[PDB]
Image (tube, rainbow, N blue to C red):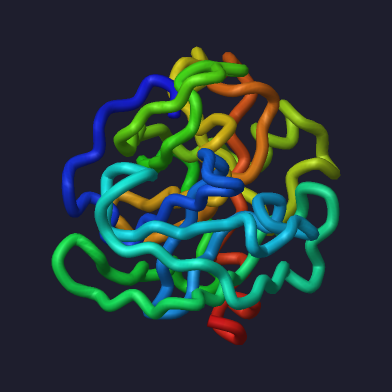
Length: 224
């Protein structure tokens, strides 16, 4: 997260860190006791055994409850950056309670309204290309950018109806590498997307691009 502030305990009860080979890698969202939603690109085709989920902590490396993975399912239409969601099943079930909870999802067919406020969180870099990552979870609030504007930045074909965009024209507030797969919520803390891709991090006039939960609810609901 670029331009972020520390998340408080209980801000995102459903957020999980996803380590790979013992190191930082991405984020995700706990949907129920045995299911995490993350970005497909975080997991597709990689050795499953390399991943460890941690829930209930502001840190990636201690606290809370961990699990390995039992299975990985990418969206059936995942291609390039498009449809960038995956369902992970956990080897160890994680109960709600305390600072752990399960995500409430954006309604099927919803699309974040341009200008509305969204909050994204993760353990990724704090600058483009940064090599260090924070120990504790960061968050940042950015407005939704219209898809039309987003297509003017990236190209018409590049932004699909399964993506939405968020950021500030000036730059300086965004998700970044290591935040992929983690949650972006609306102002009510409902899960509206997963961190997916973008042109660098926090650049002027290149929004962050998010996999849209509202658009991808059929997949999520079928396999959660």
